[PDB]
Amino acid sequence: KKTTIEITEQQQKAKVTEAEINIQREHYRVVAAEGSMLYFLVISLSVM
Image 1 (cartoon, rainbow, N blue to C red):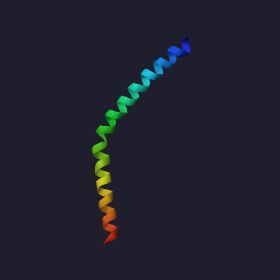
Image 2: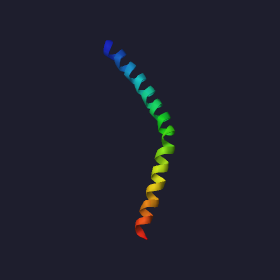
Image 3: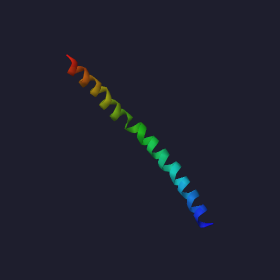
C-alpha cells in the first residue's frame, strides 16, 4: 500500500522534472544553436 503511493508520487515528480527540463531546453536552445552554427563555419574554414 505504501510502495504503490510512493511510486505514484515519483511518477508525478517525473512529469514535473521532464516539464521543467523541456522549458530549460527552449531557454538554452538559443545558446546551443549559436554554438552549432559557429562549429560548421569552423569546419568549412579547415577546407580552404
